[PDB]
Amino acid sequence: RVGIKVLGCPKNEADCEVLAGVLREGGHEIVFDVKDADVVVLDTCAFIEDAKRESIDEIFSFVDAKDQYGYKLVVKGCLVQRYYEELKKEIPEVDQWIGVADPEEIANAIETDLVPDRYRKRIDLEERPYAYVKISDGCDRGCTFCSIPSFKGSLRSRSIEDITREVEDLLKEGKKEIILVAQDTTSYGIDLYRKQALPDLLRRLNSLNGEFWIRVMYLHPDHLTEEIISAMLELDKVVKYFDVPVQHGSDKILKLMGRTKSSEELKKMLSSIRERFPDAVLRTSIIVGFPGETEEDFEELKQFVEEIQFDKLGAFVYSDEEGTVAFNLKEKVDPEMAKRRQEELLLLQAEISNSRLDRFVGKKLKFLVEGKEGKFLVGRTWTEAPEVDGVVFVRGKGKIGDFLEVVIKEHDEYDMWGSVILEH
Image (cartoon, rainbow, N blue to C red; front, top):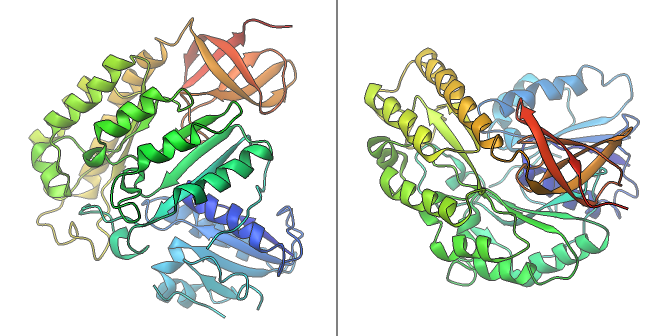
């Protein structure tokens, strides 16, 4: 028997739902992670500057109380793939260590550490109406800060049918939200179909019967071909949610980060989606204090976000990890001066977010029920994303996994409140 503690990111929370399924043979049984397990599997995140901590404080949250339930503590995930030397040297009390691969825990997690460099079934370990689907791992994109280009392998994407089969069976077991995850959704197919087959995939999935949502994440702006945009906007089952991280907005800082498109072309592309659908939700990431970031560059960036108007925006302080090309970049910036900018940019976009959630007031937005707290209902609208954005409370009745048409009343704190129309 064994319980898994998912952590890190959708991709890591996917490789768990999949692994949990494989342990139906050599595992015989999966404990509901109710702490009464025989052995424990802790998934970890490595590069996110902070998640690395939530995963380190997590190991202790388990190690501290090992002699309380008696379980074979096993640290699995990214954090162990690039910190095997340091981790095992500090926390040897654990029993096993592992990072990548999948067909290993089947004939390995049954005893043996490892970190060198087909199809399967899965099972969700919780009561959520959504499910992440990894269509490809790795990434051959030029990102001076990212260290994945040689940490999680090269670009290896699954086949349309494969991803299709998975999505198919998920819907059948009762799933209303399909979220496509990866390092870079725009890179899918290049390795298999010698071309960007992302649209071909969407068109395919958008065919399956039954009402459901299809969300796409981790969209690299430089390779967001109009063919994809027109695709995510044409299909009537693809939530118009564009999660495209630009990392920054300075012609000088972008070329340095490795990006191709400039702040100009990036705008031309973004604003163009809003013209075709003014309610389009655009979420992006940012990295302040990047090596070479100057006064002007930040003021350029600030006005950049002030112009595009992002629904949801997140800023992160640069973290030159050894190996990267940015690590070898010249003249960094005091972490204290980057933190100063991350908080100033966070304060500015905070205002824009409100203004954007203000234009959703008094409008019918598809709603996905996720829980009932009395006469109140918890859940999200196609705009909000699973435990990353916000939530939506509505006065009504229904069950988890339903699709009601609620209408927002007011908001604030990045949360909307409304009620359902058309009832019985």
